[PDB]
Length: 100
Length: 8
Length: 274
Ligand SMILES: [Cl-]
Image 1 (cartoon, each protein chain N blue to C red):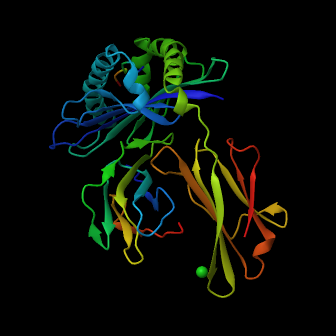
Image 2 (image 1 turned 90 degrees about the horizontal axis):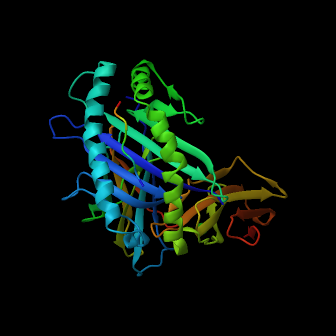
Image 3 (image 1 turned 90 degrees about the vertical axis):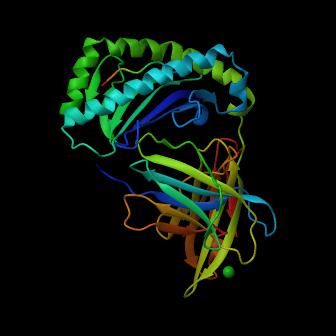
């Protein structure tokens, strides 16, 4: 089994405005095998009941999924996606950065 | 429209 | 333009943990429009766009039956591959299939697809002529023979040139408003001072569809490659896409760099500067 390591981007659906309902996305791509554990974090803590797209895969066979949840950005609240996949010894965390 | 798949 | 109808099938064994997980996804032009999921409380093909909900109820039951046949088949396939490859029991393995047609704006077939991967690697594929197979390995040669003998290629040719094309048209006319639209990107540049005397210019493109776009940075009058980053194009989740490309330039020299955004929904490309 050739395993491939997921690539991750965390980012908002609309341009972030403190205090304004938005949507936060964790876009995870280029991984194999399909089994993967994704969690979205607020201030380090699991956000509850976040939505997952239908996993699919791309022309190269590699899998991908979009995880998303409502969120309202603040000055101090921080946000992150945490990915656990066989291809990696340890879970991988990527933080939401508002100019990315 | 999807069709049926051939077995391997 | 050109358009495509595509079916993506996934089967994942999970020994001990019950029967394989099985999924089919339909795409029109890269919009997901139908889906079949074995994990469903009551599995069956279902619509994935509001426009798919308008088709005859006859549509679904038939496709659900076809998917169920595909799922029982795929379960046998997983066992078959384990046997062809002489793989140890107890692990998880995956079969993937992609099949579809790509059609030019004149309604003609540009390309038909039929291909299979095992554990993420090419297994067998129908060649462009739509008559012969390419097996990636020894194991796939056993399927190649079975499939030749069963006259599979001709079944596939007929579907890809006929039904596949005919339904693409139904679907196109169906999702008319939203499939054929163009949303041009909204662009802007951000500005950041990093260590030493460096500045990061980030050229943003938002809210565009289709997904296809190009962003470039020009210094003086030619494009750049080093000191550059571009992220892979990504879904906003509402049917639009986002991208950015950044560049690192010397401090006080920001005015010499322009960003260019190229996209079909633009009367002409965008040029931005800080
Ligand atoms: Cl700054």
